[PDB]
């Protein structure tokens, strides 16, 4: 596996979004990983529908939270997910709409990365593509991050309360990091992204609830 991987440079990552006034971070993390696979398989980079997931993954809690594994299972059993153009984001839960048209992407299930194993996470990012992960984002230091490789001793590996997308990994001035795509708009962090410490004992629980869809 390479020392460095950044899917933004290959054109495998769509523009940063803003989940608005809804706790749908999990829907954005799930579509980001599906967008990566679609691009890999077809060459087209398209915005898929987080709203489709918010409204229809009944096993999840809409704007109240949810799991990415549940979202991948729903796409598999439903035969696809709509594009953002076909099922636009409105930022509140609505009834699950059915678009008779074709779905924009499909998946054959998912895989979970072994709990706490950052080395397996690194290999999966290198070989598969962007990976959905969950972290503890409760700290003021995370919320107001601006630059550098983020590391905070108070981060709690067992308090997973936010979902994001790992789109690469690398090293900056001697510090190994993970390149993380957030869904709080481009004004947050560094143009919507954050570099999080890599190989510093699963800091913030980065490798504790990671998964990717099979396409
Ligand atoms: C996002 N946005 C989001 N996600 C979750 N839960 C998931 C986090 C990642 C792993 C799978 C579960 C949310 N649960 C609740 N909320 C609303 C906002 N939170 C309310 C509780 N406080 C303590 C933290 C913020 C979620 N939002």
Image (cartoon, rainbow, N blue to C red):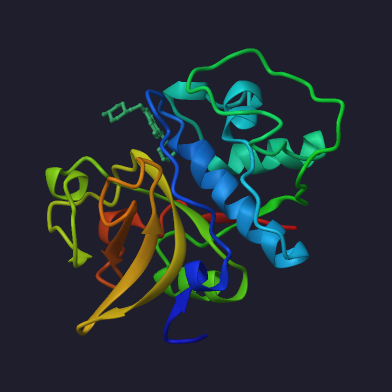
Point out residue 170 in the picture as x, y percentages from the top left corner. 36, 78
Point out residue 206 in the picture as x, y percentages from the top left corner. 36, 57
Q: Residue furthest top?
A: 95
Q: Residue at x 69, y 39 (%)?
A: 83
Locate residue 134 relative to residue 87 in the image: left or right: left
Locate residue 153 relative to residue 171 in the image: left or right: left
Determine the image quadrant of residue 73: top right
Q: How many marks?
A: 0
Point out residue 62 in the picture as x, y percentages from the top left corner. 52, 23
Q: Residue at x 36, y 42 (%)?
A: 185
Against 180, residue 163 (above or below) is: above
Locate residue 59 relative to residue 143 in the image: left or right: right
Task: Report the quarter where the C terminus lies.
Answer: bottom right
Q: Residue at x 72, y 19 (%)?
A: 97
Against 112, residue 120 (above or below) is: below
Point out residue 190 in the picture as x, y percentages from the top left corner. 27, 57
Q: Please state which of residues 158 and 212 is positioned toward the viewer in this rendering.
A: 212
Q: Please state which of residues 170 and 84 is positioned toward the viewer in this rendering.
A: 84
Against 6, residue 90 (above or below) is: above
Ligand 1 found in image quarter: top left
Against 181, residue 47 (above or below) is: above
């Amino acid at each position: 596996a390479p020392d460095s991987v950044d899917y933004r440079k290959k054109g495998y990552v769509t523009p940063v979004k803003n989940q608005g006034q809804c706790g749908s971070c999990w829907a954005f993390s799930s579509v980001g990983a599906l967008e990566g696979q679609l691009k890999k398989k077809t060459g087209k980079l398209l915005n898929l529908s987080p709203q489709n997931l918010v409204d229809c993954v009944s096993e999840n809690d809409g704007c109240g939270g949810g799991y990415m594994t549940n979202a991948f299972q729903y796409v598999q059993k439903n035969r696809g997910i709509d594009s953002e153009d076909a099922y636009p984001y409105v930022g509140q839960e609505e009834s699950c709409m059915y678009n008779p048209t074709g779905k924009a992407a499909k998946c054959r299930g998912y895989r979970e990365i072994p709990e706490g194993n950052e080395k397996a996470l690194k290999r999966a990012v290198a070989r598969v593509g962007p990976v959905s992960v969950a972290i503890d984002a409760s700290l003021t230091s995370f919320q107001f991050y601006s630059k550098g490789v983020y590391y905070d001793e108070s981060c709690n590996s067992d308090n997973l309360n936010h979902a994001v997308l790992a789109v690469g990994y690398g090293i900056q001035k001697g510090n190994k990091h993970w390149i993380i795509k957030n869904s709080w708009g481009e004004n947050w962090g560094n143009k919507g992204y954050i570099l999080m410490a890599r190989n510093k004992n699963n800091a913030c629980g980065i490798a504790n609830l990671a998964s990717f869809p099979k396409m």
